[PDB]
Image 1: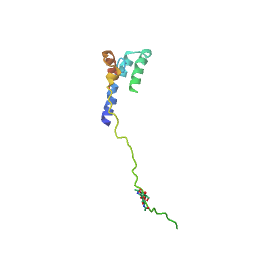
Image 2 (image 1 turned 30 degrees about the vertical axis):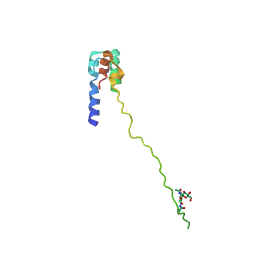
Image 3 (image 1 turned 90 degrees about the vertical axis):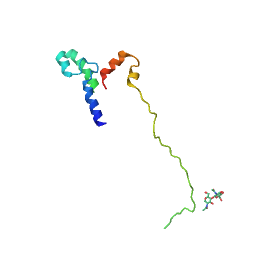
Image 4 (image 1 turned 60 degrees about the horizontal axis):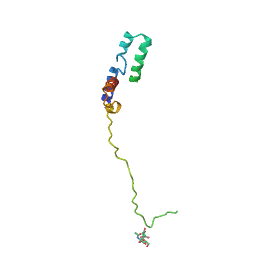
Length: 48
Length: 49
Ligand SMILES: *[C@@H]1O[C@H](CO)[C@@H](O[C@@H]2O[C@H](CO)[C@@H](O)[C@H](O)[C@H]2NC(C)=O)[C@H](O)[C@H]1NC(C)=O
């Protein structure tokens, strides 16, 4: 049960939650701050 | 120097009631959230596990 809870928490880092990419560095390489903050708030909300 | 000793008795039966289980519901997430929509079912996969 502990290992399954941690595996589930780690696999959730790979989810998009509605952002263009589930990788934070893709958003910050591809996008400038005004639009990038919109993609990052989706990842913050999903990861939180 | 005083003691009281019971000279008779009563057998009492007292009921006690305890919960032991509860209804085994299961709610399927995709059928609850979306229900037959493929459009919704695809959006829900972005939220992962
Ligand atoms: C102890 O108490 C019981 C009743 O709690 C007594 O037996 C009863 O006595 C009364 C009065 O004589 C009768 O009307 C009842 O029919 C009896 N039986 C029951 C089951 O209540 C008993 O006599 C008492 N004994 C002592 C030690 O006094």
